[PDB]
Length: 224
Image 1 (cartoon, rainbow, N blue to C red):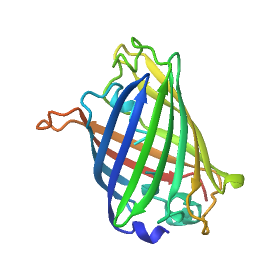
Image 2 (spheres, helix red, strand yellow):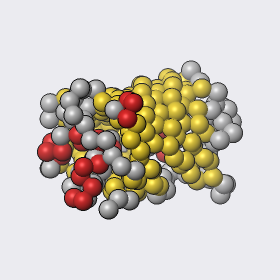
Image 3 (cartoon, rainbow, N blue to C red):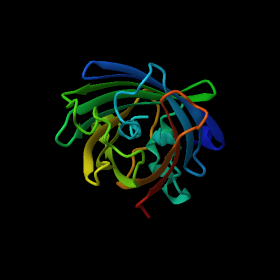
Image 4 (cartoon, rainbow, N blue to C red):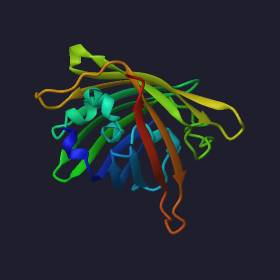
């Protein structure tokens, strides 16, 4: 449970993707500090050029690192499922474009918190904002509301991400998310609340590979 997150925890992220038949892989490494809600990660496209914009993968690429304030500890499903972990599945529909479907397992593998993901993308436009790489390299603040899913013994969430387009417009990405536990022990099913997240995206000047350096802060709120 939550005791696995009292200090800084190494993170490994692995993604295998296929968007419109364009196959790619991403590896990320870094660490998470749930006491401050902080993620520091570097992601590399290990197959060459990433065929979608890095910001469209941020939500897919570890909510167990959210900072749950003491008065909300009983509502932290994500840490309660550890070390066995949880499955996280999303459908992400890009307005006037294609959709992603993702399945991930988030679980401890020894001393490392691992997020291992399979992503498919369907019916994107080669000239659209995604395959056409028309999104700014940034990721706005968002709140995601978390509700219990008692039948699945987990949580669900749906939320819209606003991605800035280079021409000043916005590209919406409508997320539906469902999480379940991998293990069969007791988990914490939350009252309604939300997570507030901010991200800063950057580039390592000495990295020639297609990559994303990510800072994130995730904080739970919305309960008494």
